Image: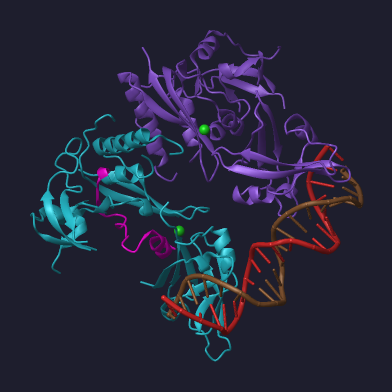
Chain colours: A cyan, B purple, C brown, D red
Amino acid sequence: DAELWYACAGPQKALPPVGSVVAYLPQGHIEQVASFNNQIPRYNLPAVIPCMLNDIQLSADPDSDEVYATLTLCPMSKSRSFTKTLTVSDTSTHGGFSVPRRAADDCLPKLDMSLNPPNQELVAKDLHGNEWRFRHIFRGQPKRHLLTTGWSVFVSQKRLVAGDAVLFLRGENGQLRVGVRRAPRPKVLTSPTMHIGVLAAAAHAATEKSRFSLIYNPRSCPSEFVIPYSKYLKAVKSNFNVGQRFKMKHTGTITGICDFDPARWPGSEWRSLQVNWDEQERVSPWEVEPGNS
Amino acid sequence: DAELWYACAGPQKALPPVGSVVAYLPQGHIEQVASFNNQIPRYNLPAVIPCMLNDIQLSADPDSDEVYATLTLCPMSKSRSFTKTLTVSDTSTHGGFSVPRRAADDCLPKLDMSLNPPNQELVAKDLHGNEWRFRHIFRGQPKRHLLTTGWSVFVSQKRLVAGDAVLFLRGENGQLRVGVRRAPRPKVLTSPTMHIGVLAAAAHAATEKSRFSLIYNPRSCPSEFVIPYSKYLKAVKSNFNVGQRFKMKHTGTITGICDFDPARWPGSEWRSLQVNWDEQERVSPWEVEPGNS
DNA sequence: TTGTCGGCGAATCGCCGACAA
DNA sequence: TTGTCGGCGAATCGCCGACAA
Ligand SMILES: [Cl-]
Ligand SMILES: [Cl-]
């Protein structure tokens, strides 16, 4: 289910539609793969590459549960939801799970309060179609919504620890969906060979106008690097200036406008906005909005 | 400890020494990275690349325990040991671990048989220096060597299942070492971008005579692709012929001698020997020996 | 509102010879 | 030689209100 995939990725995540023109930004692709590790031949590669979004394949690791997507590019010429950060008691083998009162009313199905105690056995599917059975009971003094039977098994099988978060989604159907967003945490190739591979594949696809492929790792990608081409153009046509107040979907002030990496990426709009927050320091024009909406 | 690293990799594994000339075989490097997944721009890349072995870095995944090495190449112009495949009872929460009688005598320290029952608390370090305490008891009827206290914890923490194997090494020192060899089982880059990255990095290093780097995954590499250059030359000078009997460090018969992939790797000695076993079908001259020693 | 706790009953865990392959 | 089993004692597991933040 695609709604579950975006929930585990992040609330502000929504990939461009297949068949639409997108702006491929290689600086951001490298930033993603460089976050997995810690010079190279210089390629004549443009800082932006308009591409047709040929295909998207949402995927999830079975054992680890991390979500990722495979995108195919070709260079050119809603539902009720809630998330809770798991506490120590939630993950402890001692007790069960404390359901936020707002979540049980706005997300979980309504219990029969005429029962004593009100209870139901919920059944939720994860990203791989596996069913999970939870007993949802309303007890305690003061009274509360708890998940008892089936919760600790869910904790051990998915190896959940405190600080992690559990997700629940209820669509129009009675079926429930459950997800996991783990707290922040080179096996096949070294980083320079990964770095070189990204450039050469993009270069070959750019000069030949042939389609290539990449992996999107949402929870390991600081800034999206496949954005709608229209959103990219409207950002370029925008004329930011020093001292302007901006906002992010947190507020700050633009302190400068210059290139982020003028050595190998001259004239690039990537992270070209020097900013200072009010309470990371280099952002792109398309991820900010003038701070007076 | 380097002895533990090679134990977890495999008995027939021993990398060339640092500072020696090695034969880099890109066909085998691709075979390794293609085993992690399931067309590309053609590169003028030779089937063998003599390189100086600049550095080796043995490493091990902390959580998963898989071993890998980072090698740095530059193109040019002993101890008592035993291994047991873990049974169901070994991994079951029910009992402990059955130590093979030959292992306790030839590897583990000698128990004081004057005790009743003979026992000692062993302390072994894993690949990351963590200590593991096991009670080694000699009991049962018929009598046997068992590991009781500390074994089931070792099973749960390392997530061991039946079919996996445990290793133990005893050097000249009293300190013991323990290892794990798990049964046979794309996150950051797609396979074509991995494929392209291997070629381009090797190509750039070959034409510029600059040093590059790669990852060796022993338990995911079917045939070694960084071998001593002398061993490669002596294989080329060898004149195999059809019908010759060969042996592998299993015996068979050579049925043909031709190129393995004449499309993109013409005139390559890689897997250039068609063989038929007596009881996989394409091997290289340097991994076989005439079957009459 | 909700995280943590103690309390017991339920249950898995773990060490021990008893047995065949 | 050694894998699996039953047997109990040891122990963690799990559901329940009681309590403050
Ligand atoms: Cl899916
Ligand atoms: Cl080491």
User: Left or right of B293: which side holds A112?
Assistant: left
Q: Is residue A100 magenta?
A: no
User: Considering the image in quadrants, where does the N terminus of chain A appear?
Assistant: bottom left
Residue A21 in magenta stretch = yes
Quadrant (top left, top right, bottom left, bottom right) of the C terminus of chain A: bottom left
Determine whether, in the image, residue B169 is placed left or right of residue B270: right
Q: x%, y% of residue B195?
A: 40, 34
Vertically, is B235 above or below B160? above
Mark yes or no: residue A11 visible.
yes
Residue B111, how many percent across, how many down?
79, 36
- Work out whether residue B16 or residue A8 is closer to the camera in this orientation and state it: B16
Region rendered in magenta? A1-27
Can you tell which quarter of the image residue B219 is in? top right
Q: Residue at x 78, y 42 (%)?
A: B119
Image position, residue A85 (x, y; %)? 43, 66
Residue B224 % position (x, y): 53, 25
Q: Is residue B42 visible?
A: no
